[PDB]
């Protein structure tokens, strides 16, 4: 299998993570982990078995926790799939998620090609 230095993944992928963060207000619900107590939604962790958010992805990328770049792609799509699963299609959060996913799909393709 192919070997990737943590520093190579960090430098290559950080611009794509910035592209998500800079979407305002769409990234705001995704910048920190969903807090079901604060939001009053105790069933969140029953429906969403594997929570994910931008802060967790950013920490994994900054600290060298990904073995290969498709694991970062996996985490980003997990984040988006969790939001589309939990929230109504008509809801703000679902629509914000769809904006972020549109940004991500545009940005991630050339980066993954260059990482080989
Ligand atoms: C700016 O955008 C919003 C602002 C408020 C709401 C309703 C309340 C809220 N409703 C939220 C819903 C989610 C969420 C996600 C993401 N997936 O399932 C759920 C539920 C996550 C966070 C949510 N939050 C917290 C939001 C983002 N605040 C954080 C601190 O500063 C002000 C805004 C929704 C949105 Cl989309
Ligand atoms: C593009 C796209 C759109 C939507 N929309 C939802 C509703 O609104 C309209 C469409 C949902 C998606 N779900 C996923 C998805 C993954 N994609 C990989 C892709 O990024 C990718 C694939 C090959 C190479 C590269 Cl470089 C990147 C991977 C794992 N699990 C996933 O669910 N992709 C979706």
Image (cartoon, rainbow, N blue to C red):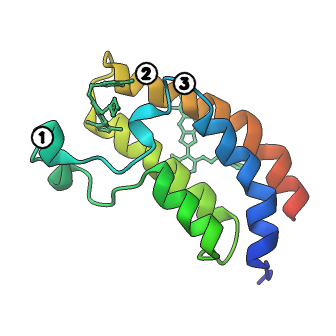
Instruction: Please tell me how crowded label 2 is: few (under 14), some (14-19), or many (20+) other residues with Cα within 10 Å.
Output: some
As drawn, 45 above or below 83? below
Extreme residue in the right direction: 114
Q: What element carries label 2?
A: helix
Q: Where is residue 42 in the image (x, y as percent from the top left)?
A: 9, 47
Taking the spot 62% from the left edge, 55% from the top edge, the residue there is: 73
Q: Is mark 3 on a helix, strand or loop?
A: loop
Task: Identify the residue position indicated by label 3 in the image.
Answer: 24
* Whole-number angstrom distance, CA of label 2 to CA of label 1: 19 Å
Q: In which quarter of the image is residue 31?
A: top left
On the picture, is 24 further left or further right than 109?
left
Q: Position of residue 116 (x, y in %)?
A: 87, 65
Task: Identify the residue position indicated by label 2 in the image.
Answer: 95
Viewer-closest of 17 and 43: 17
Quarter of the image where ligand 1 sits = top left
Task: Identify the residue position indicated by label 1 in the image.
Answer: 41
Which quadrant, please, contains the N terminus? bottom right
Instruction: Tell me: is circle 3 under 8 Å from ligand 1.
Output: no
On the picture, is 107 further left or further right than 27?
right
Q: Where is residue 90 in the image (x, y as percent from the top left)?
A: 32, 15
Taking the spot 43% from the left edge, 51% from the top edge, the residue there is: 53
Q: Earlier in the sequence, mark 1 or mark 3?
A: 3
């Amino acid at each position: 299998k192919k070997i990737f230095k943590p520093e190579e993944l960090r430098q290559a992928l950080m611009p794509t993570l910035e592209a998500l963060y800079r979407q305002d207000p769409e990234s705001l619900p995704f910048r920190q982990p969903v807090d079901p107590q604060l939001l009053g939604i105790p069933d969140y962790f029953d429906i969403v078995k594997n929570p994910m958010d931008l802060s967790t992805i950013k920490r994994k990328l900054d600290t060298g926790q990904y073995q290969e770049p498709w694991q970062y792609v996996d985490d980003v799509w997990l984040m988006f799939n969790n939001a589309w699963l939990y929230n109504r299609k008509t809801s703000r959060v679902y629509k914000f998620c769809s904006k972020l996913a549109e940004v991500f799909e545009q940005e991630i393709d050339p980066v993954m090609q260059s990482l080989g």
